[PDB]
Each structure stands twice: as structure tokens, then as C-alpha cells.
Amino acid sequence: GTRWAVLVAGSKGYVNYRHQADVCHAYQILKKGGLKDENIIVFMYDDIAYNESNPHPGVIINHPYGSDVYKGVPKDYVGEDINPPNFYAVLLANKSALTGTGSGKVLDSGPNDHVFIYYTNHGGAGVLGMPSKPYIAASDLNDVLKKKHASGTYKSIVFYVESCESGSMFDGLLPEDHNIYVMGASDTGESSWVTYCPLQHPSPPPEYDVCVGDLFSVAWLEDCDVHNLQTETFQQQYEVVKNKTIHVVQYGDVGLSKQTLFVYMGTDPANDNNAVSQRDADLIHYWEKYRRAPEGSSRKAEAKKQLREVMAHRMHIDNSVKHIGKLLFGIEKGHKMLNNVRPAGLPVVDDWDCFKTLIRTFETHCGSLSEYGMKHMRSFANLCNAGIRKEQMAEASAQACVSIPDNPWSSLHAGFS
Amino acid sequence: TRWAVLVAGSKGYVNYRHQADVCHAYQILKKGGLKDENIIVFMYDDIAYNESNPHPGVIINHPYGSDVYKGVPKDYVGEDINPPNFYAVLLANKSALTGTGSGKVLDSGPNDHVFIYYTNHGGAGVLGMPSKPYIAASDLNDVLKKKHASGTYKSIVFYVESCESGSMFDGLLPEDHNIYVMGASDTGESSWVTYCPLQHPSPPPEYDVCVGDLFSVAWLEDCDVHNLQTETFQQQYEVVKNKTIVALIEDGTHVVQYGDVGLSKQTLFVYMGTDPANDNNTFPRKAVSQRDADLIHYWEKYRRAPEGSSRKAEAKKQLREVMAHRMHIDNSVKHIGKLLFGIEKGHKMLNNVRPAGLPVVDDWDCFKTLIRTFETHCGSLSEYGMKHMRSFANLCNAGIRKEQMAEASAQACVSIPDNPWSSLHAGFS
């Protein structure tokens, strides 16, 4: 049987160069390995290669001393077409439910085929980021994987995930008897990290404004760059990635971790037998953009405005969420309800319908959480688990947070995360 | 006798810059031969043994520099650095001093020369002090007018490192009072800072802050390694003018000279001293704005702190508090401008530059009252809101009164933000 791959970069903007650059790198490894373009579905917002802020138009790098990885990478789903429905339809091999200028390439696999799913962006508590709202909820995701299993159009599925709280997407949801092995960068309650930033041990070329790669991703991308894939098992790769960090989780059928990396990816002429927070990295870019601009320049003026708009939004969202906590529970016992971690083995939330309505009512009074407010998704999760209903949140979210601030990230134009 | 008055108008580890300059200045004068008894040092003693200092007991003013803190006198430290004390020290009036001061004053006569150097930061015709209130140009120049009348000095060189430093003397300091001035910036221009964490000449990596100001450093290095008998003040001016490499890069920021410029023909030996050097004068230095330099330190203090640590949490909080206060002040001032004049013609009134030769303001009594009424509704301007002192100046010149300002400053800015820089505890800049 054939070997497929689904690669997903859940972010947009030059700031998040790293996520697309990872996906590009991933395609290069698979191409070298021998997988056919026709079986590699690429979701990437095509806005980094030819960005105005890119020093080297047409090239993307995933390493300080790297060369290009962008050339020849397919563009199946780009721009606004990267939405969960398309991703879900692409997973379920349903071409009749795509929307946009997509390629039509789907996971039309059979029961002898192996699939390697890769997604990096980003993420929050039971939610992965996408470049076009709404985002991917864990309930919706696992329902699709449950349907795919029922259809029996795959033997094995390795799913690698680079996002904050990435364990929370599967923990208490993904069954272990479905031939789906997961390798997350973080557990339910922890951040993912980013390497190769402007000021670091392995700093990228000085012309670069941004971090060029994520830590967990880069870890496994390097391992599958210079190693025979017939002499290395997924369990080994897990150990390798683990040693790169300063938790790497695995979920689902961990029985599949005994297989080699050749069954999904491919080894070429090799024959060689076997960092900062994601949210905190975005600020490096803005500060540097405003810290590397000529004084009294238009760039400096815009860079400074962008930076003020970012900081203002993060302070706004944090305050609002904190305040709503104090309005629902108390000032000294409200902090705990929001910042709580549920015992390992349970889902993030029981009532997902509630989950979404709470986030939406928060947004209809406060605005949008963007990609920075995903930090507080667990807070909303905990509220739905505490038994808070729309009528009770709506009162609380209107009292703290009466004004939606005039920020570009607080806009609701095609919003409601 | 040769006297000197050094002033470091600021406090906090952020402004390591300013005190490090004053330390360097004392070292030059000491080597040059001036007696401690005739060197009055105003420095808020909070840098040498700060918790954020990687090398306790040492201050540096150069990336490859060694200590300049050792042996520097401490005449006025802590909260005693206020304009009344500075003014009493200038007028040799020990009877009007408040605090744990040394009591050292400018008890000079008509054959004496004095070198006054103050750096911090500064606004439109006002210099920063470490404890509010600040030094207003009107009050400063009145003291220099009083000193001249007493006839207890031959010549006074006054060096100034602050934003809009020209505004302190422009249209106020008379040119026949034997006072020569050398500002770092003219009336409407910022001063700059070199030797920051990420620069051409970056300081030792353990350092978290810029260690020196551009203008100050320029003349300090010149008086470090030259025979002061073979170099005049005009030459030093030309030296410093070349050292500022931002003159052509950015706007304004022209090194300026006010008062009796005739005195610029004297040698630096009359005010300073030249030790074993004998180097007859002959013939990149990258740098950032003063208000911008402060952000380098906060960001760097939050970008180096270990993730999920106490430091990070506090560095992050401090950074949010700074950014929030700066956004607040800017908004409020801009808002009051649209309320007083218009939305499209109110921006020009606030950001105006008066023709060279005129003072910043005509009515100084009004000037202070407008700042105060803005502060009684909005909070304090701290050291960042000195950027809008010219705005208030333009309002006083546009014929705005307290009653009109109080209404406008109450409608824009109804709340005082709960920020540490918005506090009024011993405030009212």
C-alpha cells in the first residue's frame, strides 16, 4: 500500500514564519524519502515566501545555516481555504465538501495505506490554531478521526503536533484502539518552544527579523534529515526529541511506536544507523522590527504602532478574563478556577457545545482572542466544567469588559474563534 | 580656584547612563588637578550597589571601560537632589539646604572659573530631577542672573545632556554674562545614548542597560586623552559635533552653544585639568533615543529572565506598566489637543517649534499651572511625559488658561490609570 502525508501550518503573518518553514522542511524530507506529491497534501498560508518583510524573496529556511526549503512544495490549500471544514473534508476524502480555490487533493486512502499527519502553529486548551477563524476544536477533530476509523481506510496513522497545550487535543478523547499514534510537543497545560531566534545560541542570519523554527518540530526534522529510516523506530525518535527539550507526550495506539520511520517517511542516501515560548517569540519579532528601524522613519512609526497594538491587546484580554473570573467566583478563589489543570486522563471539557458558546459570548463583549487569547481557552474550559451557562457569562463579560478596544486584533471581521 | 558642579538628574537602574557620566566627569577633573573640596557631586546613589548590577561597587562608562565609581564624592545623594538644593548650592547658600547633605556649596569669588555639567532626561525648557518637582528654565536662568549680579565668578562653562536642552537657554540666557553653554540637543530635538546591549560598541554581556550617553561620552573621551592646554572649547565642540553621527541620520539633534560664546576660545585647562598626556589635538559610535533606551532595558530584562520565574513575572509586569503609561499619556495629550483646538488643526499646535531666538514660553506661571492641572486629572508625566512639555508650552502661548485646560483634561482623561508612574506621591512634575 501507499504512503500519504498531511502537513498543516495553522498560522499566518510574517511573525509565524517558523510554522510554514517547518511544513516546508517536512515536505523536503518526505520528497527525498520517496513519497509522491500526489499523496502529500500541504496546508500552508502562502504569505512568507513573498512577504515584504522577507529579506530573501522566494526562500524559506528552517535552520541558521540552512538553505531553502520552499521550492517545489505543493500548495494544495493556501490563504483563507485553510479552515477546519476543509481539513476535515481532506481527512475524510470528501471532495464534495471543500470550499475555495483548493487543489481537490484529499486523503483518498485504503486499508493498506499508512498516513503521517503533521501540523504546527499555535494552539490552546483543546484547540489548534488555524489561519482563518474558526479554529479546530478537539471534539470536532476526534469525531473526524473516529469516522475515519469506522470507514477503515487506513492501517496506521502517525500524527505529530506542534502547539501549546497539544496534549489537550487528544487526552480523554482519542481512543487507544484505533491505530492512531500521537506525538505532541506539550502536555495539557504546557507551552511549546521556539528556537533559532534573533538573539540565541544558534542565532539565524542577521538579516532575519524572526524566529525561523520551532523546537519540537526542528528536533524531529533534523533527526529525519541525516538518519537511515530503516534503522530507527518512532519510540527512538521520541527519546531523541525528548533530549532536545529543557514534556514530549504521546497518545493513542503507542503500540505503533515500535514501527520504523521508513513505513511513513523515507530514507535517502544516508546509511547512518541511529529556546523561548511561542507567545513570547512573537514579541521578539515586534520589538526587533521596532528596534531595528531607522529613527524617525515610517517603518519605525508603523513598527511602534504594531507593537503598541499587540501589547495593548494582550493586557486587555488578560484583564478581562481575570475580571470575569472575579465576577463569577470571587477575587481570591476566582484565580484558581481559571488557572486549573484537570487530572491526567480526563478531557479538557465535558460539554463542548457550552465551551464554544462561552468563548463566543466572551468575544461578543470583549472582542477576539486572536492567537494570543488561546492561552485562556482552558479558563473557559474550566468555566464550562464549573457549570457556567451563557446567561451567566454574558452578564459577567459585559460588566468587566464593556468596551471592545479599537485594535486590529480585537476586530470581529470574520472572527469568533 | 577651579570649581565644578556635576548633576545626575535621574534615578533607577534604567538610567545607569546618567550617573556613570557624572562619575567619569569627576575622574577627568580629579586627574586634571581639581580639588575634591571644589567639586560638588549630585548623584542618586542607587547604581553602584543595585540588585540588578552584575558587578557591585563598580560603574563603567565604556564597553571596554574599567570602574569610574571609586573615589567620587557624595555631596547630595538620594532625595536631597532637588532644585532648591541645586539652586542653594549654586548661590553658595548653606543656610537654605534640606537633608543629609555634605553642605558643600559654590562658595566662589570673582577670579574663579566653574564647570557645571548636568545630564538626565529633559523636556521643553526643563531638566529632569530625581525627585519632583523639576528644574524649570525660568527658575534656572533667574538663579544665573542672580549669580552674575553678585559677581562671584569670572567664567562659567555649563554642559548639558538632555532632550530639548537648547530650550533651557534659548531666549533666556543673556550673551554677556560670561556663561558659555554646550547642549546635546536644540529646542525640539532628542539626545541619544550609546553603548547599549545590542550595538556597534556593545558593553559586557552581563550588562542589561546602556552605560553612556552619546554627547556626554563624546566630550568625556576627548578630555580623557588630550593635553587640555593644547585644546580649546570651540575645538571640543567640533570634536563632539563629529562624534554625533546621528546629526545627518535623524533630525535636529544639533550640538548647540548658547550664552557668551566668546569664552569658547579658552583652553580646557582653565576649567579642567590635563595630566600625563601631552597629545596635541589633531584633525562609528552607534546610538538610540533616550526614551527609547529605557525600553531596551525593560525588554532585555524580560527577554533574558528564565521562563516561568519570579524575575520574568516582575520584568513582564514592569514592561506592561511602562508601555501602558506611555500609551495613556500620549492619548490624553493628543485628546486634549483635539478638544482645545480641533482634530486636524490641534496636532500642529501641540507639535510646534517656535522660531529660534524666542523662549519656549512667555508666561512661565501659566506653564506650570497647565502641567499641574493636566496631572490632577491624568496622572504624572514622570520622565516620559517630558516629551509633551512643549505641547503645554504651546498651549500657554496659544492663550489657554487653567479653567479651559481643566475642562479639557477632565473630559479626555477621567480616570488616572492605576500605574506606578501615574502615582502622585510626592509628584506634580
Image (spheres, coloured by chain):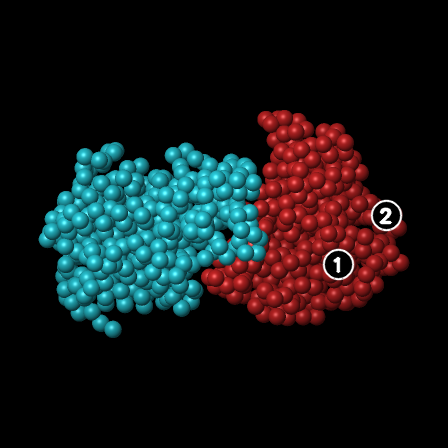
Chain colours: A red, B cyan
The residue at the point 78 percent across, 36 percent down is A354
10 Å neighbourhood of mark 1: few (<14), some, or many (≥20)? Answer: some
Is B106 rendered above or below residue B276?
A: above
**Residue B423, image quadrant:** top left
Give the chain letter at badge 1. Answer: A
Which sits in the foreground, B168 or A45? Answer: B168
Is residue A303 in sight in this rendering? no
The residue sitting at the front extreme is B399
The residue at the point 74 percent across, 46 percent down is A416
Locate the C terminus of chain B by quadrant.
top left
Name the residue carrying label 2.
A147
Give the chain letter at badge 2. Answer: A
**Residue A375, image quadrant:** top right
Is A163 rendered above or below residue A321?
A: below
Name the residue carrying label 1.
A80
10 Å neighbourhood of mark 2: few (<14), some, or many (≥20)? Answer: few
How many labels were placed on the picture?
2
Is residue B107 in sight in this rendering? yes
**Where does residue A181 sit, x and y in percent of width and height?**
74, 48
The residue at the point 61 percent across, 42 percent down is A316
**Where does residue A248 sit, x and y in percent of width and height?**
63, 46
Amino acid tagged 2:
Lys
Q: Is residue B263 left or right of residue B61?
A: left
**Where does residue A390 sit, x and y in percent of width and height?**
77, 34
Amino acid tagged 1:
Glu
Q: In what element is the residue under mark 1?
A: helix
**Where does residue B74 sit, x and y in percent of width and height?**
23, 41
